[PDB]
Length: 130
Length: 240
Ligand SMILES: *[C@@H]1O[C@H](CO)[C@@H](O)[C@H](O)[C@H]1NC(C)=O
Ligand SMILES: *C(=O)c1ccc(NC(=N)N)cc1
Ligand SMILES: [Ca+2]
Image 1 (cartoon, rainbow over the protein chains, first blue to last red):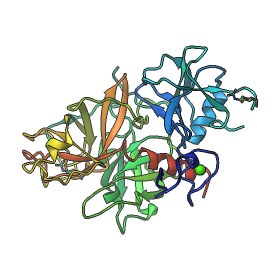
Image 2 (tube, each protein chain N blue to C red):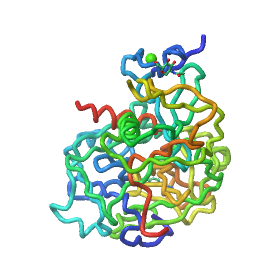
Image 3 (tube, rainbow over the protein chains, first blue to last red):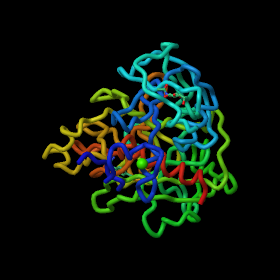
């Protein structure tokens, strides 16, 4: 019995758009920033893994929506395409014909732009020296 | 901070002084204009009520923290699985009534992302107004010092901390001592620089004494608490 704890739900019920835990923990941590280059990643319930988001057709309102999902509210700093350094082999591509952020993406083994989204929701980590 | 040096303006713009009864109690880290990362042991009862607390940002000297410069705390959230006995999951969040204005003096630190690939002995910094010697008084000036990460397996050796380091904990400092956080630094930042960005990898939690050999500082593993932090900010974002 494959399962994930809500503190136990089934994998396909984690990040599927329907809240199965009493507090909604199965649907409120499906987007994340990966690595020192802030690679935007989305959890796939089918493959039980995190996949980077292609730069294809990505715009700032999509990044703002991702920033809201992460709990940063209206904070938004930047969004640009970069080369993936997360070592991923599968990616989430945006489907134009759509819906929610995590529900508008589909799996793909390449990005047309050859780039993944690098998303920074807040200007942080900068001090006096460089 | 023991064995460190006084901080320059804008050197640690995320460092915040948390006050109760016109007195510095603990440190904190700005991550958003409203949210501050601090230690759960700092907000144990009776200081779990938010109206006891005032945050001071962008000010290096305690005597310069005048009446009217501080930000009233609106909300205090302790980690649900915090254990006072073991200091496990020693993390808490503070939300301000009024958001901070960001400038070269007051800026947030970045929450750690998964896949940081930090070195086992990664170079880090700690800062705060803690005592500069064990059992000493709160320091007037903000201090800071360099410390190295200590692998948990080495830290859990019977000769260091004997299996008291949980996966929600990281050790930093020097096994020889002489450079360590101290009383009053708790809740403050343990930061590291990678990809020209300062990351908050730890919040000052506890240690055996100060700067003692084979008793380095123990810090809350902010990477583990990242999921909980995002949920709290978001939950407050949807309003309560
Ligand atoms: C994209 O949207 C279209 C229209 O609904 C749909 O046919 C298709 O399956 C979606 N995803 C993929 C994998 O193209
Ligand atoms: C908090 O005030 C605090 C944190 C950690 C220590 N111990 C050591 N760094 N050794 C003391 C006090
Ligand atoms: Ca679900």
